[PDB]
Amino acid sequence: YSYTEKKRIRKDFGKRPQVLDVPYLLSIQLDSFQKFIEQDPEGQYGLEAAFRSVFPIQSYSGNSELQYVSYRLGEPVFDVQECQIRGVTYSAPLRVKLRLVIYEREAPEGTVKDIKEQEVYMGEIPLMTDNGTFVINGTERVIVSQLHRSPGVFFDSDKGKTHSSGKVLYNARIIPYRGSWLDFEFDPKDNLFVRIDRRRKLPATIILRALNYTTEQILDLFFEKVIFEIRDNKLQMELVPERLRGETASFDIEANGKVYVEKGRRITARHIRQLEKDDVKLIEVPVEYIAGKVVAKDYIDESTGELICAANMELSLDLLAKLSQSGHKRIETLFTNDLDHGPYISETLRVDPTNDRLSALVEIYRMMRPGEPPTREAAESLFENLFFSEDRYDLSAVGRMKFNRSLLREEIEGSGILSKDDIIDVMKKLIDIRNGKGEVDDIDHLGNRRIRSVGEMAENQFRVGLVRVERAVKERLSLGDLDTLMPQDMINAKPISAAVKEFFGSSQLSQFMDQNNPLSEITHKRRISALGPGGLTRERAGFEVRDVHPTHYGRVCPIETPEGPNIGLINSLSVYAQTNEYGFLETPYRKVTDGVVTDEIHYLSAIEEGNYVIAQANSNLDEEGHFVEDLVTCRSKGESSLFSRDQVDYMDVSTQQVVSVGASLIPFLEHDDANRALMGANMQRQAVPTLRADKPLVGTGMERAVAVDSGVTAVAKRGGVVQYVDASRIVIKVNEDEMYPGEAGIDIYNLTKYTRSNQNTCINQMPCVSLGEPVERGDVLADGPSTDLGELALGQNMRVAFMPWNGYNFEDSILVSERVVQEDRFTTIHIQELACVSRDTKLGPEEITADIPNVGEAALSKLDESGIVYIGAEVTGGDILVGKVTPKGETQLTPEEKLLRAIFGEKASDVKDSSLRVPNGVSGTVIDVQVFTRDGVEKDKRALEIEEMQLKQAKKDLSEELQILEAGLFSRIRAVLVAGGVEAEKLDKLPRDRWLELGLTDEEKQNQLEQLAEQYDELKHEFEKKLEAKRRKITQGDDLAPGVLKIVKVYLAVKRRIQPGDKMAGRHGNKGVISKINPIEDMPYDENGTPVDIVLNPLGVPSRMNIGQILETHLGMAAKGIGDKINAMLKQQQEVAKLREFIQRAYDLGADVRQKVDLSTFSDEEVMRLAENLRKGMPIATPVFDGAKEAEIKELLKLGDLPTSGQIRLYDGRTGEQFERPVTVGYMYMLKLNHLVDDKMHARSTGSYSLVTQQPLGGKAQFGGQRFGEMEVWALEAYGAAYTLQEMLTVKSDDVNGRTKMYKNIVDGNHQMEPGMPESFNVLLKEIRSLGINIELEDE
Amino acid sequence: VPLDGGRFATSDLNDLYRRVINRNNRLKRLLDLAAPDIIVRNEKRMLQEAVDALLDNGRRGRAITGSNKRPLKSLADMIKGKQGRFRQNLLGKRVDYSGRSVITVGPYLRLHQCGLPKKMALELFKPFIYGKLELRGLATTIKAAKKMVEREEAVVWDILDEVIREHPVLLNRAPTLHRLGIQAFEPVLIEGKAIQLHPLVCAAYNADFDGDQMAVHVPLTLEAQLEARALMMSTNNILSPANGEPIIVPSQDVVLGLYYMTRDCVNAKGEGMVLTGPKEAERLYRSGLASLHARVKVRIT
Amino acid sequence: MLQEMGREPTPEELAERMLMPEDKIRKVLKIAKEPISMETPIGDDEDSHLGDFIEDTTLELPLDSATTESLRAATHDVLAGLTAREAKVLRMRFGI
Amino acid sequence: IETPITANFREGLNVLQYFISTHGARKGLADTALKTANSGYLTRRLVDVA
Ligand SMILES: [Mg+2]
């Protein structure tokens, strides 16, 4: 095992041999950004996709253009933490090369013309960590991924819109990535119509004119040409027999001489088969058969050029005769097998009055631009720009793909542009399924559904900024001088950066980090939503997308989402799932071959997955045979069932990939209900890292793999040995093999001490290790606020018991003892930020110093000469922190205070106090601060002090840095002397600086001398550069806001401990609040006096069914026992070999375990420290579904020599007798919360008010009044407390004279009311009158 | 108004007033100058459009925004939805002399009693105390009263108790679905920050000790004091008006312990003996002779 | 000057180039802002628009009214123990 | 649904059994998250009348 694993393991009950070592998990957005930065040459994405989509660009004249060259970034100016400190964003310089290429219009293309081939800076750009977030102004933040609807195409059919009918109206929509949508739609009257982006209806056939087509060219396509021919008297026609199919005969339908089908007789497949078989087409038919048919095409007389029958016009016997008289045998007509082939299009065509394409243009223009300006080029360019210009329309070739495959083409690609064949194939297809064939799809199928990561959206807004500039570009291209206008003489990058900062700061998604918990942050990262632009809405979206499609299986954990309006909307990703490069999704699946499962996989989509059959992982192979049971629960078709065995295509890898993470971490969920599960994993994320890192005991196995890729602590980049250790930092020696030649090969790791989140709780890091010891690579260095040996540790493993008490666990109510508090394992810590500004005024500059008027030196006692607190102190509400004062004017006072000042001689100055103080109700320890001051403002003395002190701290360690680094390297400058003799003690005792003056030789040994001089030079020079940079930026002042002069900030420290009302829970929805804490005496207790830790009324487990909690309790009750066996073996102090036996047997108990290990491989001391970690109780890993079972539990309990029920007598602490009966116990792992009453409870005597109504506020932060709803009024309405009603209306809110009078009456002892009339009333009167109304009162 | 940063803040309407001025100015300014009617028409359109915008931004047509990209709030919008005077600011109101906190149980308590973290009542009963200290003249006037308050003298608490006696108080949970979802109790003080109460009335409040919390109000005036003590005193309220239903059903545990008690095994022991009365029954079982669940003879009166 | 620098210019060298001191620069920069319209949702959920936060610190506080009234009445009580000419002088001379 | 459940929480679910258990749970919970709006709305109108 790993050394970290050599020192502590976790038992496991996995039996199913797992295929996978799960992937890296923060892969996704890191790679998204990596795309959006990285240089694609050709298959452009993001950055380059936007550029190439844009450049080059010509003038509005058509003279001059400008061209792309290349891009690059700078390294960011600064490191990270200095921005954490300054409250700044880190970001890289953007520069872009460009070539201002123009061509002589004098020549045709005489490119002997202007080329400013220069480069530009424009726009710094928020860069990424190695963990993904972007810090913004000292704010760690998270922009969030999205899912939404894909471009391409989507068809639907609303079922009984006007349900008066009960009819389907099919309809279609096509959506680009940019540009206009488009809608096709039916009516009950079997007529197609159209609208863009919800414009109005239009009969689609107008557009067919608009697209330059004729009725000929249309119904050529839509219909076949039913030809009649009149042979010298009589009508004949070729007939496809399967036009008369499920149809009825009108006249005696006979043959050349033979009757197949009489009148009124169905043309049975018998006689369809005959007409085929006997092979007749040319069939005598009565001429009447035409009458009612429509003419296919415009026919005339050649001598006339006049329609005797117009195209799409009904035929008649007079027309029959006449058209025959003009000379016509062949008569093309429509084919109307209304069952199959018939009227939808001719209907709308007749309904379509635009004789010509030209009128179609007119009325298009008109509806779109209502009014009467018509000209041609307007509508022409209009239409052309809608769907046939690159400017205002693009598919996202994703959409092209999806569209082509709705079309069943073979080209994934095209343009972002239309063609007319496609349009008509659509209209066709639409009509075709209107005849009955085909279907529409379910959006809930995830092949309709595409993600949106960052580079996409970044590209979007970036392109927009490019266009914001491009407007000006055209304007200043065609107009300005051409020879001399630089390319950057045109540029303003401000709209660009504006868009950046907007999206990087003004998006629903662009939000803070959720930081309390590595789970919280990392699942906040692997979170998904679908809101925002081209997104959804609470009011409008409904259940059906909130409800699940089975396609989710393996791609989306259904388990994990918030609870309220955001319930079915917000969802995270299942574990082993990934994306289509398009943005669609995939999951891997194991192929199934001949019964034998193929150990390969493939990343199937949502769609293929339905086609194939797929198997599970609960499945039982026949030991490299096949599925044992004939009937194997497999699945295809959007549904599962039982199948045969070699029949199968594919398999699920694991039992797991369906799920995601907090759901994953819970064992015995199989024994648990789902509501409780969702809630438990929901508040699993509301963690609190406690004072130490106390593990749990039951596991699942993933938790190690979790603890790492938070990035929360260091790892072994390179195995080695520890040089140096500090309470703040460490230093290592890298192994030679890992070391590279030029580099020295040593790392430092300087650690994270007490610091804050967005959610403003402690931060700290520290080593789990010792020094002068080997290290393997990839290992950890230091655990964190909630971490332990590379494994999470958030809560508290301890004891549990189950019983009611005297009303101290009534309804969900939980109870506890006091020793817990002595162990203060729940005790935790907080900090607050406090700061202030120095400003310049209309009177003068504000200032700070100890000098204040009317002071008690009590407060001053702790403040420096600059008027500022010294460190180490403790403070509480009302104390002073910094004495700030502001230049004041002058005023006057009443004769009474004049009488006061006139005898005491009370004298004053012309300045006001504006000094910082502790807020009411707060106290804590003074530990750290800072100051910021302008480059331009004198740094008030102690600023310089800490400034200098900063140079003390920083440079010292930088000294320390080279004091190691540089130092070691000089081994070379010594060591290479050893060859060719060596000055054995004439080297050492005399000074090292004069070793150059020792023995020297010719040819090869002056080269070493100048090598020495070169390293001398370079090595001192490097630190000179360091010093320069560092002392500068530490000397760098502060670009303050205009009027701001310098700034101070401070931090205290605060600690918090446990109390009733503080909320509590574990891992099942098992909430609770404390109503009491118990002295240990009256605690019930056991035969052995070892009393209880926790009490709980058991009643609620059956109703909520958090059953696995019990199972946990059993297991932990066991596992503690073994730690105790061990514990006994140590004071008793047994031996090696007995531990050897006992423990080897111990972990070698279970039925069919997967994991396997030997013990003699290890040393003694490894075992010693291992057991030393384990004496408290054995850690166990429960895979949820491949977990352990009842039998092994009871087995190992019997080894623990315990009652199998674990259900035992107690004695009451108060009476010392026994209770009635045995009671269950064990160990469970328990957890506390954010929801702390200290952060909650609040009263309001009398304080701040509103400003227009002068009504009290709301908020503990603002001493806010509490609100009184209508409902609360209605209870009184039942009751009738008219005086109280009056009271609460008037003086508690509105009546000012009233409230004041009452204040006095109460300090007078008087409890006597006065009303007035509220403010908001007369406010509203003035409002009415402002609206030109004579509202007015009728006085008594 | 300005802000501490020197930063200023306005209402929508000052724009719209401002708008019209200039147009009317450019009306009259033009009307000095003898224009074609067409421009006048245009101008009047601008004017009455602004007028509509005052009365309603988004009624007749496409609404009007600043660089917010959002509409400017109508005069009408001040009266409107909930947002206007009616539902926000007039019928529902913020209140002085009220508070809130997380809550918990008093199993020991009686009806009229209620757990009270004391600072709450402390700051909420201040002018009682200031009239009272002027009366005692320890604090002759009120500055010193507050000073001595900061000084934390034991007398305060006695004085505080000396106030608080017989001074009823109001209990408040939301959502308030019927008149019984709030109540009126008598105060009881405690060295904690979790409110203890008589659990049964969760049945009334539909409440549970799983993260619920509540708010509190004061009957200052004697009329309110006595209305409280007389009307939504709980002894005056035990049933529904919906039905003749006892609303204080013994909820969950008392029922069960009692069920277990009044119980007729045959199994335990001491079968077929005889008593005088339940006092010796206590003595007898409590001696450890007997079953509390066993049919055996006794006398009653 | 941003093309020149490639970066943001300081008031220092820009006051140099613009040929007049950082005084006027900063004096200007106190002006460069516009108002931000009371009713905006700094409550992200439509829960508290900015206008709802402010208190009006203009009027007075009742406790301080009682303070100053107790002052005035105690001075009445004191001056009541004075000679007639004294207190009448001392009243009308201060307008008490 | 056609195939009912066999195991319990004493025995332990299948993958699929819990997968399926998901659904109506979510549904009725969504309903639980919205009937109060209509409730308050209606009752408000009721007082609005009388
Ligand atoms: Mg509740």
Image: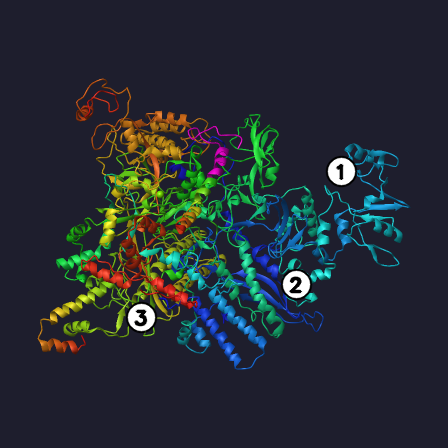
Residue A710 appearing in the image: no
**Residue C32 rendering spot, x and y as whole percentages:** 43, 71
Closer to us: mark 2 or mark 1? 1
Say which mark, if any, is on residue B216.
Answer: none
Q: Upstream in the sequence, badge 3 or badge 1?
A: 1
Magenta span of residues:
D1-25
Ligand 1 is in which quadrant of the figure?
Answer: top left
Judge by depth and name the residue closer to the eye, A169 or A31: A169
Q: Upstream in the sequence, badge 3 or badge 2?
A: 2
Which residue in the structure is indicated by mark 1?
Answer: A247
**Residue C12 rendering spot, x and y as whole percentages:** 42, 73
Which residue in the structure is indicated by mark 2?
Answer: A366
Amino acid type at image mark 2: Arg
Give me the residue at 54% from left, 28% from top: A621
Alpha carbons under labels 3 and 1: distance apart: 99 Å
Which element type, helix, strand or loop, lies under badge 1? Answer: loop
Amino acid type at image mark 1: Glu
Which residue in the structure is indicated by mark 3?
Answer: A846
Where the N terminus of chain A falls, by quadrant?
Answer: top left
Alpha carbons under labels 3 and 2: distance apart: 66 Å
Left or right side of A798 for D24? right
Q: How many residues crowd around disc 1 within 10 Å: few (fewer than 14), some, or many (20 or more)?
A: some
Amino acid type at image mark 3: Glu
Tags 3 and 2 both on a single chain: yes
Judge by depth and name the residue closer to the eye, B265 or B168: B168
The answer to which quarter of the image holds residue A434 is top right
Q: Is residue A565 above or below residue A554?
A: below
